[PDB]
Length: 295
Length: 294
Image (cartoon, rainbow over all chains, first blue to last red; front, side, top):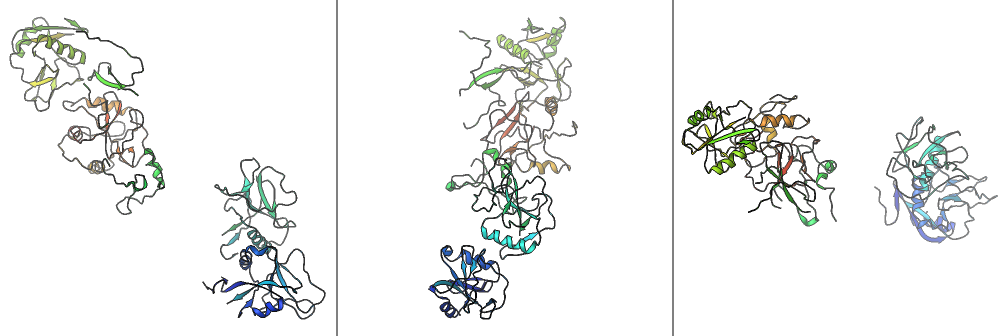
């Protein structure tokens, strides 16, 4: 519950804040090293914190991050710390020059990839102040021959797809393996929407298909990770062994017309058994009665 | 002449009335009401002895009951006996044409508790007059067409003489007492008849032959009993039984009743016509617990 001062969003003790200043790499290294420290990526949730902030990420812009390298050959080490665990670079521009004493690195793109610019211009940056994901868990089973008998995985955004992708890549080490996603249709018409166990009517926002995946007017799609990693594979779901990850007043009447309806409620002590509005349709519907009708 | 069993009378598409015959029933001549867009029969039009396989003889002599019996016995004749509504109406109209109250032939055995005709035929007709009139053990046909209970050891201006319980895995009971409780009559009956013996629920209809059985059992002590009660009351904002069980055999007359009151009158007809009557006064409870089916 660590709360910071007017803008620094916290996550597990520390908090971040983006500065609205456009300056070079040396001035940024001199400003937040303000009594602050530059940003360092160590987990998966902070990537979400960086992507959801930054004013729609300012798609056509770049963000700084402090990475230094003085000795040759190339050897990246953080300015404050040595916990090198996560590297998220663009595919695939390493931008590693021949030889240069000052090194720099920048968030590019909406996904938040890492690139190596010349850091001779002025740009914005972020600095700090002093399985599971952070809000929900993700469990996987040993074998799943049937199709979704215990869980039905549902996805909403692209970052959740990236998170499940890196989770399954940390789990998977070989090819020839399939997964399950919430995308199927039982009407055999062709419309594809976010599948569920009944009662799903949301509109599809994002989709990652291959060059030519869909060749069947139905079925339940899959997810492979051999070469086409992170994309939706299509295949029939009649009997297909594939695992899946699960996110873890005449007489005796009382009423009032202030709601334009005659009510009938009971207490919690004078009654025989605790009564609610659930099964009232078995008893009150004989008089044309329904739920609490307030305008 | 609206007998309160087939018509709903309370605080209130044309309505037209007719007379219904029920194939020699003890309540012949009932008035029903329906839509008169259909076709029916017309029999009578009003402007300004042998009868129905029976024979009748009237004597205008003034004499007692046994004297009239001896007077009719010489010609092989027996005193009158009312067991059908048609012959009852004929006897009444003949008495009115004679303009007098004539003798009726019958006798009891034990202090006017078990009345019986002189033919030996099971009782199937009752047209008594009043309850607080049983002073003696004889009856006389009056002008209004009822049976005034008096002693016929008198001198009438004439006489007439004619010539021609365990059942289906359930046990019932009849209570003849006096009660005055006229409040909270929807949550006491179960605890009332449960104290008598365990496993005793209110009468529920789950078969089809119990109605005829209780109908044949009803006309045994119907001297002052004419209505039949039911166990259908206001339960769970609906018209159901007292126990926590749904209803299967519908007992509605027509349309769809929407009685929202805490109680009403579910009655059984003479033939089995399902009848519901909404009440505004509680002065129909005579007839609810004293001499009725509980």
